[PDB]
Image (spheres, coloured by chain):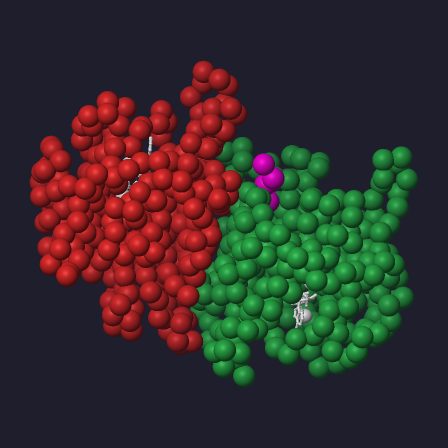
Chain colours: A red, B green
Amino acid sequence: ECRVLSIQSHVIRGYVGNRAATFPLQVLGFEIDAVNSVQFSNHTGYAHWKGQVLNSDELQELYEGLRLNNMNKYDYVLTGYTRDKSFLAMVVDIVQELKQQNPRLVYVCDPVLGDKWDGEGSMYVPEDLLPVYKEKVVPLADIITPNQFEAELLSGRKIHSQEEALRVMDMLHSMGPDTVVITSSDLPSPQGSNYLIVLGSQRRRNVVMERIRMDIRKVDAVFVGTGNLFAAMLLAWTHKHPNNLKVACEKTVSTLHHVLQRTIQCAKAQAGEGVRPSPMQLELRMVQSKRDIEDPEIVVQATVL
Amino acid sequence: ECRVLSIQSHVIRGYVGNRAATFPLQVLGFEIDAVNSVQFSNHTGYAHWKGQVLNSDELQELYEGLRLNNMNKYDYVLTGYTRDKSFLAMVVDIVQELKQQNPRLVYVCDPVLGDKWDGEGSMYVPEDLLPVYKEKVVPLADIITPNQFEAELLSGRKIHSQEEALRVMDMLHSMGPDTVVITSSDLPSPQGSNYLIVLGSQRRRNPAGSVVMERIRMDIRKVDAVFVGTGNLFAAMLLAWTHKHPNNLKVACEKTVSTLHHVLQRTIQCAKAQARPSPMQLELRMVQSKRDIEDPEIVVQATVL
Ligand SMILES: Nc1ncnc2c1ncn2[C@@H]1O[C@H](COP(=O)(O)OP(=O)(O)OP(=O)(O)O)[C@@H](O)[C@H]1O
Ligand SMILES: Nc1ncnc2c1ncn2[C@@H]1O[C@H](COP(=O)(O)OP(=O)(O)OP(=O)(O)O)[C@@H](O)[C@H]1O
Ligand SMILES: [Mg+2]
Ligand SMILES: [Mg+2]
Ligand code: NA
Ligand code: NA
């Protein structure tokens, strides 16, 4: 049994954070325990939203209960979006402790900080978080999944090309994580302008390095939860395929493809044909993608670099 | 799309409340939205447990969020263990409005009040809840899943034989729900002393327009151990299987009870292997019962009443 302590948001309607991470990991047989960092009616991409958060003391309270029963032994830890600096610090103390309890623990960190829209990036988290991430979180992380913007912020240098991107990943590797994966980038593709690029690098002794590239066909709308889903599925596939970033990223990415495909279709069907689908209609068709998650048909071959 | 609003407990580790009802319903294709009434480290049957609870005001706020985004359109509402009277009264108003929004909404209500342990029964929620359930909840419920003790508290009648059970079930129908299932009772079993009894009663109008009633009975072999979350699982699967077989209580129940069996069988084996088994080893082996949840092999046929 593989246990995962996943600490992320919970929303009542929709799929983001733990909602996007849990089902798929459960479907793939993991014992994922979800610590809901917040509980909102839905994600902030909607016009409205209400909810309550979980403060650092409550997080600790929860960990203590787990400790008391000797349930503080996990195989992986998964974290994503957080707005509170106090919360992040508490998360760090927990991974450290869980790591002492089980040194083999793999910490999967999604350093959610911001994104680039047109080519300009803007953080959607307070700045005081960046240093914590650079100095406390990443060093403890074994696997990190930043998008292009987050990889830039974390290293201090802009990524203009693929080679610059790979240099930035090298920097992150030295910061601690043995597995780095850029989940999206403005990088150009020879396949056309309708593409976003994914880059992945893994450091594993034998020391041997593995680097892969993937050119994903862009879809018309804006999704929410896909980053979180990418992180959880990476966790899942690097677990079944350790020492194979290639396949692990192919299954991860193929899973997302199917899900988004199913989502964009039903989304356009509901929305009046010719009309841009709303955030509500654009919620991931998670439940309906069950079979694609269990065994994703590979539809994007990754090229070795 | 079949949308379910499930307001129940959440735990980090283990499967009870919403943790026991979500994965299975998701596996079965339902868009189940979970509103976590509490967030504990684990269920209260463990030596220890820490956590926070959701109070009526925050529930209302969470509801407000859905409302503002016009996402308060559900096909089913599902509730279970509720600890606070003002919360239950909030759950009641919520359901009342969801029903105004969609008259076809089916409220599946598991009236958690207590259970028989010795030969005696005792409550495990504030006694000032009983009147609320009697006067506000049950009247709104369409499907209720009380155990024997609860069917007695709601009816103000004690059940000593199969016939008093049926009499009580009729009383329960007159209070509101068209479907009443007694999820466990001591009652005599032609197959021995180690058998708990399940009783089902469903009233419905058939095509012609005649109001009829289906009655079933099931004798389950008692296993030597205490499980937590199985009541929640029973209700969850009841919802799901009466949804597929609306005019057939026999099949819905046989499938519901059969799933519990499979889950319980697999759970007891991995418990004996690890051990008496503590609460932790008797945690329902949920993720591992995926197949059985999807297509449960009927292993206990119901006798018709
Ligand atoms: N518009 C899209 N078209 C095609 N694929 C997409 C699209 N949006 C997201 N994806 C899929 O989701 C993956 C992650 O991209 P996304 O932008 O959602 O997350 P991110 O910004 O990289 O990370 P995060 O949101 O956690 O900071 C992409 O690699 C791709 O597989
Ligand atoms: N010890 C057991 N042996 C066999 N089956 C069991 C056992 N415990 C629970 N079950 C299964 O779970 C079902 C519900 O029983 P359980 O006692 O868990 O809930 P309940 O007491 O009837 O209702 P609630 O717990 O919600 O108040 C039983 O009908 C049976 O299908
Ligand atoms: Mg992005
Ligand atoms: Mg019981
Ligand atoms: Na990312
Ligand atoms: Na019950």
Q: In the visual, does A163 lie left or right of A300? A: left
Q: Position of residue B24 (x, y in %)?
A: 56, 53
Q: Quadrant of residue A16?
A: top left
Q: Is residue A198 above or below residue A243?
A: above
Q: Quadrant of residue A74?
A: bottom left
Q: Quadrant of residue A214?
A: top left
State how many labels appear: 0
Quadrant including the C terminus of chain B = bottom right
Q: Position of residue B83 (x, y in %)?
A: 59, 63
Q: Position of residue B11 (x, y in %)?
A: 48, 62
Residue drawn at (14%, 52%) of the image:
A209
Magenta stretch, main secondary structure class:
strand
Residue drawn at (46%, 33%) of the image:
A262
Between B183 and A82, the one lying in front of the other is B183
Q: In the visual, does B286 lie left or right of A1? A: right
Q: Is residue B165 above or below residue A41?
A: below
Whether residue B48 is visible to the viewer of this picture, yes or no, is yes
Q: Is residue B41 above or below residue B118?
A: above
Residue B179 inside the magenta-drawn segment: no
Between B231 and B81, the one lying in front of the other is B231
Name the residue at the bottom extreme.
B276
Residue drawn at (88%, 46%) of the image:
B212
Whether residue B111 is visible to the viewer of this picture, yes or no, is no
Q: Position of residue B60 (x, y in %)?
A: 54, 46
Q: In the visual, does A137 lie left or right of B279? A: left
Quadrant including the N terminus of chain B = top right
- Write the start and end of the magenta stretch as one range: B1-6
Name the residue at the top extreme.
A274
Residue drawn at (69%, 45%) of the image:
B243
Between B122 and A15, the one lying in front of the other is A15
